[PDB]
DNA sequence: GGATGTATATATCTGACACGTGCCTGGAGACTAGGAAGTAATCCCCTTGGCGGTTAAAACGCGGGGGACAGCGCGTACGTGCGTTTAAGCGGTTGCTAGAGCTGTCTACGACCAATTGAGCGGCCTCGGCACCGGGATTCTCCAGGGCGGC
């Protein structure tokens, strides 16, 4: 998911723009991948339950 | 008829009991201070019974070969016994010194107490270094015009 679907230009190494619109995830992968998801300029957060 | 085996009595040896004495250490009596028991408050860790999700460890099965074990041979090294040597064990000399025990004197060193202050613990601000964002320089892919060929 990370290197085939996050970025429009995943093979670059400078500023990588985002490709997806909405990312659905769970709490376990918020805790597991906070380093790879906290460094994203999110426009909206919706926390269910 | 003579000497031998055995029983009872008497003197001597030896461990144990009680008497005597010192002395010094434990006990009795009194006083005091502080160690610890008890109390209240605050805050953080542990308990018991659950749920959810990841995932790597645990469990199970199976094939195969490496290793444990048994047996056998062999040769060597240790046990065994005897004769010989030697040194341990005991008793002994002869002086001097080390050390335990006791008594005595004294002095420097450590306990103790009051005042002081400066080194240890916590937080706060700043720097060294790492990292995020904006701007300039360099290289790669591409769309269109000019020229040539065919019916």
Image (cartoon, rainbow, N blue to C red):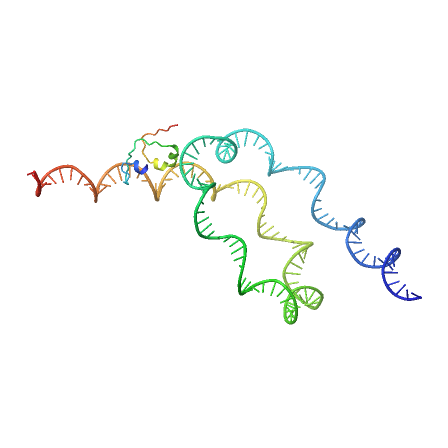
Q: Quadrant of the N terminus of chain A?
A: top left
Residue B131's spot in the image, x, y percent? 33, 40
Q: Quadrant of residue B32?
A: top right
- Give the residue at x 30% y 37%: A4
- Give the residue at x 34% y 37%: A36
Residue B103's spot in the image, x, y percent? 69, 54
Q: Is residue B104 left or right of residue B7?
A: left
Camera-side residue: B38 or A9? A9
Camera-side residue: B97 or B109? B97
Residue B100's spot in the image, x, y percent? 66, 56
Image height of B117 relative to B105, above or below? above
Residue B9's spot in the image, x, y percent? 89, 56
Q: Is residue B29 left or right of residue B128?
A: right
Q: Quadrant of residue A9?
A: top left
Camera-side residue: B51 or A6? B51
Image height of B87 relative to B40, above or below? below
């Amino acid at each position: 998911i990370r290197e085939y679907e996050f970025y429009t230009n995943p093979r670059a190494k400078g500023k990588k723009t985002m490709k997806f619109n909405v990312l659905l995830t769970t709490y376990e992968y918020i805790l597991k991948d906070r380093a790879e998801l906290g460094s994203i300029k999110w426009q909206f957060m919706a926390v269910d339950e």
